[PDB]
Image 1: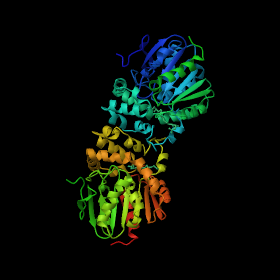
Image 2: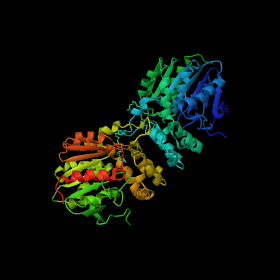
Image 3: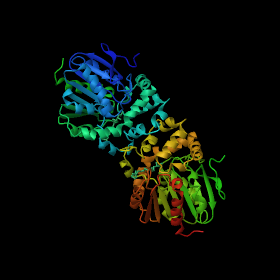
Image 4: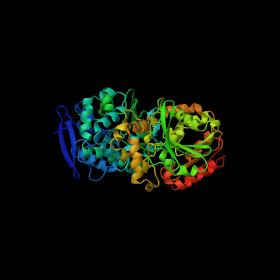
Length: 297
Length: 297
Ligand SMILES: *[C@H](CC)[C@H](O)C/C=C\C/C=C\C/C=C\C/C=C\C/C=C\CCC(=O)O
Ligand SMILES: *[C@H](CC)[C@H](O)C/C=C\C/C=C\C/C=C\C/C=C\C/C=C\CCC(=O)O
């Protein structure tokens, strides 16, 4: 069974990594690019970008542990723990050469530690729409002069007593539509049909729980990154952020400048959080061009 | 019929104010003191203080519009709109003398405008455990290095699509227990019976909605208060806040200093948000002593 339709010429497959069965979709030829999705979604957020990248790269898009069709992690959900799975997965397909990385939302949290600990393995890096977990997140406001802030879900999802699963179970499709659209500028790309696909996936009980365990580990990830950040990233990096409702605006680049020696950033107007879907044409162009500066098929 | 047991010597009654039938519990003799409850609760949070105050004052404890047994407002839920109902209710019982006011949590939001606009009507003022709505609330953090913050409910409750009603319906007792205990230092004061009573009251569909409409009007209340705050409060004021988990600490008095010329403050160590229940005896003492400096029975 497949939760989302595989683009023509791609394969849906699984690979056991440290006892955890990870789902991924792979296609193309050439140097490897790994694309890592975020909360509320799966590999499928990349499905429009993947055929274009596969003209020049081998493309792999895994489901994060516990999400999509991937088994939950056996170690834990902190960034350093999850990054081991993703690093080992990528290195199975690119054992002798560095690979490229594109990551969205908590995909950043789940890859930053393996990037900084294995810098020679990462040729080029693209990060979009999430802070790297550090002390800056403790200053984000709970409430804004416009109304509800974009990050109160940090506390909701991290709350104990399984608060979020208990309130959202049985209402997953309602919650996800509200959550996605509230973080979007171009909301009407989120058709009922597309929302149905995403909601059915994260409504699996272990996936609903996995979704929130990433946030229950957020403070641990901050503590991990306080040590890791003592070494700046040396590879070429690009940040993308939405400029519209739901977008991180200038924060994405400004934080990354503290982490990376070589970074360029873009803010996409009229685009919110969900860049691959809200603003596919400019986002895909920016990613393809940036990765194509390095060698490719 | 009664949602909560009435203390001996008190009467549960109703008055129509601007076409809205307000419920209150009243007893005692002497100058009037009005006690105004906050979110998650009703007049009943005052039921231990009421008989002690009734020895020297006429005591009235209304249910906020839409909560407990009070009808929803017919104008709206902003602080200025709700304060009209509370002011006119108090004036029905104290038309010829200024009256005292004690307010907790959103009881502050719903009384501050009528205090600043009718200062000659307010003899003494006691405010506990809530910010007056102003720009300071936009600095409260969404997330903390210890887990969920105390203020992310501002955004949860203000969100549209009836997000809070939809997620909490069928789980009203579960949510309220979690919410109360996460804002408490002393959780043992919240018995099964007490939580049952509060949960059944705010679970009434119109009361569940009313609870969150106060937050959907919060930014409007902020904007209203920006104009009202040009006039400082001149009457004797006391602030109270918890010093334990859930408490506002020094914020309560420090904010009130910008609003009131004559203010004294206390922080109660070992107490959280729910001061009348978590720390009934010292809270009662400080309120009674502060109000008894003025002319009473
Ligand atoms: C996934 C979310 C679905 C992760 O949990 C969180 C990742 C991103 C959160 C989405 C948006 C965050 C929005 C802004 C927070 C940072 C500040 C923005 C800086 C300047 C923009 C100006 C402004 O609008 O205030
Ligand atoms: C009713 C809540 C049930 C109202 O919606 C909110 C009123 C207050 C909630 C309780 C506390 C949070 C309020 C504002 C936070 C302000 C400052 C907190 C700073 C430190 C004091 C103690 C601490 O948290 O360490």
